[PDB]
Image (cartoon, coloured by chain):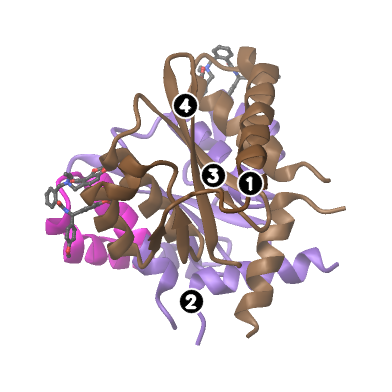
Chain colours: A purple, B brown
């Protein structure tokens, strides 16, 4: 669906990269935080849902599913908070391969900035613009614009 | 044009809110920083252009236009950096009205969070979702989707 996103948390350089993936398109937003907490996850989802029409979030683990602070942000922003269980088994693999691709890109730009957060945003840019043909950034806009026309 | 954005810097609580407005739709992204510097503005433009197809940015003042860090980020991300001179005088008033409206919304949410950055992101969400009839978040997706189908 146009409104469905998946949370994903990966580690690099002793830091955490929190990723939101729009499942239908593969488009992503990401940020670097010192560690995953409910307050950091809640703030990231509030940012995401002010930028895209976020209807459902599959959370990345049971601590973020349970967290009262995350539940409060999902309430505030009108998001249905769901678990992230790969009922479809091809979902573990899909996230795994995105983390590996992101980390590959980060390493390809890593010497172009001191701080990891800059490299991660260069990787977000390269990921979203990569043509596979349409890019993920093209796909998400097409999907949502098609939705709005209904 | 679908790719034209304008930077805007406003102050509150001794902090700076940097805003990027997509001119054709009124859609915005914003962040709080302790002060405007070339490095903060460059990082913010890198974030923006990994999320939307940013072709041109009208910078908010001549220091950000001149800044080599900002010029480096615009080169990296494929952005044409422009001045932000209101050759059309209505532009002045439009940005001022947007600052005033943002600050009004921030005041309306201010007690719902300790940190100003949370209130600013609540204000971004309310601004982008407000119907004027379409919202700014609907307008930007439809403008860009129409562009992609050319
Ligand atoms: C004085 C700037 C500080 N720093 C210097 C630095 C430190 C180490 C290595 C490189 C650099 C460097 O100069 N890279 C260029 C660059 C130039 C040519 C290239 O050609 C292939 C590629 C990249 C650059 C310019 C603007 C950018 O803006 C998006 C990002 C990167 C860059 C920086 C800016 C803003 C930030 C940062 C950082 C950071 O280092 O992380 O962190 C948060 O905001
Ligand atoms: C223990 C949490 C810390 N803090 C407590 C606090 C401190 C002061 C005032 C209120 C609160 C409060 O509990 N607000 C609820 C709330 C509950 C009911 C409502 O009904 C109208 C409206 C808002 C809230 C929950 C999750 C949110 O997530 C988007 C935002 C806000 C909220 C917070 C979280 C994450 C952050 C923050 C902050 C912050 O204070 O700025 O800053 C960066 O990431």
* For marks 3 and 1 on the same chain, the one whose residue lies earlier in the sequence: 3
Q: Nearer the viewer, mark 3 or mark 2?
A: 3
Picture disc at residue A135:
2
Q: Nearer the viewer, mark 4 or mark 2?
A: 2
Which image quarter holds the C terminus of chain B?
bottom right
Which residue lies at the image location 56% right of the left edge and 64% below the top edge?
A23
Respond yes or no on whether mark 2 lies under 8 Å from ligand 1.
no
Question: Magenta residues, as a range?
Answer: A97-124
Pick the front one: B91 or A130: B91
Residue tagged 3: B29
Q: Nearer the viewer, mark 3 or mark 4?
A: 3
Pick the front one: B45 or A11: B45
* For marks 4 and 2 on the same chain, the one whose residue lies earlier in the sequence: 4
Picture disc at residue A39:
4
Subunit of label 3: B
Subunit of label 1: B
Marks 3 and 4: CB-CB under 8 Å? no
Circle 2 packing at 10 Å, graded few (<14), some (14-19), many (20+), is some
Pick the front one: B118 or A14: B118
Separation of marks 1 and 2 at Cα, in angstroms: 37 Å
Which image quarter holds the N terminus of chain B?
bottom right
Picture disc at residue B89:
1
Respond yes or no on whether mark 4 lies under 8 Å from ligand 2.
yes
Where is residue B149 shown, x and y percent of the image?
65, 83
Q: Main secondary structure of the magenta part?
A: helix
Where is residue B103 shown, x and y percent of the image?
63, 24
């Amino acid at each position: 669906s146009p409104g469905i996103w998946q949370l994903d948390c990966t580690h690099l350089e002793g830091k955490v990269i929190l990723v939101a993936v729009h499942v239908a398109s593969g488009y992503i937003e990401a940020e670097v935080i010192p560690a995953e907490t409910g307050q950091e996850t809640a703030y990231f989802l509030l940012k995401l849902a002010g930028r895209w029409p976020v209807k459902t979030v599959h959370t990345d683990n049971g601590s973020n599913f349970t967290s009262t602070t995350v539940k409060a942000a999902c309430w505030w922003a009108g998001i249905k908070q769901e678990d992230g269980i790969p009922y479809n088994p091809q979902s573990q693999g899909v996230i795994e391969s995105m983390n590996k691709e992101l980390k590959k890109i980060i390493g390809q730009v890593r010497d172009q900035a001191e701080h990891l957060k800059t490299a991660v945003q260069m990787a977000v840019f390269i990921h979203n613009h990569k043509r596979k043909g349409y890019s993920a950034g093209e796909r998400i806009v097409d999907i949502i614009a098609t939705d709005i026309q209904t």
